[PDB]
Image 1 (spheres, rainbow, N blue to C red):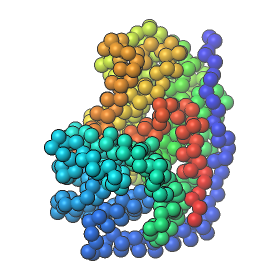
Image 2 (image 1 turned 135 degrees about the horizontal axis):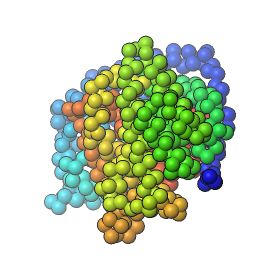
Image 3 (image 1 turned 45 degrees about the vertical axis):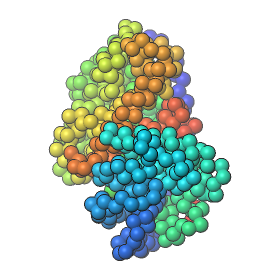
Image 4 (image 1 turned 60 degrees about the vertical axis):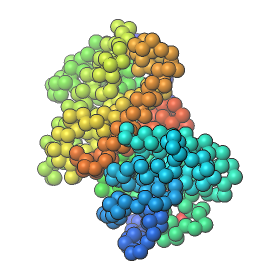
Length: 536
């Protein structure tokens, strides 16, 4: 058996993450000051007699500065009061921000708040085109709509064309904020990534900045970064000691990029155990993917698939040596998870992730069968298989394992494929298919999403990519709707699903596979989040 020759780029990080020693004196100093700044900030939020516009701007600033996770109760109480008092008497700037903030927090504020800014025809008044802060906030708000918000149908196009027109003559840092927003809206960005940009490029350069908030944000970002580096060191050593880099050289070596993925799902310190469990799974399923896609023979992949279904160390001997390596690593990883969750009495929840992993591998094998047979399924059949091969049902399930508050009922809800999860999975599927179409096509993969779409509907690549873009837009509206109260589970368990969809948008920005090719997109993010501290 002569295998397909390896074409993946090596890890561009080497060992620079392998060893990190926290400076305990600096850490304790930061924490000590943060506690003080945190209280000053809490008192800013609980201050009586603030105007609506001032209250919304304070909350928005604290959220963009990445420090709102300290104030979830206070912020929720304030937005809840604003929701219930129903103040519809403001300018575009305040109205659009009110709408976005309430919607992002699950408060179903009516989109009729925008009627006064539109003409008889439902189109935004073009007289608003000279109000740059109104346009910017309308732009950001336009990305949080549901299927019930067609009054906002025109908002993205309207704000975009006029922000583009105004941008070159704006003062700084407003110009840079607008320019950034047009490339990456806030709602669909990875929170740490957007926070890092906001702190260093915008708020640090604002003449009006609050000094207490800016210092708080910098110390907190840098203190959390220390934790992330410890985690990544710990994960880098784990990966190094598995040595897939040499024993499975056909596979993508991307444990840092996998860590960036897990960091996108949640960054807070209470999810430290969850992040570390998650990155290990993302890493390991990546190995399995490359085995199906770029190395294993039809017969080998059949044995591997069957062994995964049986999930028994007795099955190893049915496998080629090189498959024994990953199979044992997989079984051991889940034994690790079980032991790690023992003292909290949560070991039994590991089986939910295992069953999702089995599902991914069955569908990998189907995809391989399709390839060998030269089968091009209809789109409905394609999706019934290819949705799971995104790994996103599996990653979402995995994200709950290290979350101490996740219960059987939460896993039960997730197991039924709720709409918000299905949407996030669909976004991953259609975005990846649009970006990897040409490549997979060159490699003879006739069952690619876009190809199935073209053959099924009898349309061009352009029309098919446009139809896939529509599916992604529909799915984002489903995600936004899925966040609205009353939620079927705690918001804490919805946000990881939302964040998975954000990571897709951020990683495949400009229609390129950033995970397989980290140099262009992921490398700057990893440097900003995990290498360079914010200068104070």
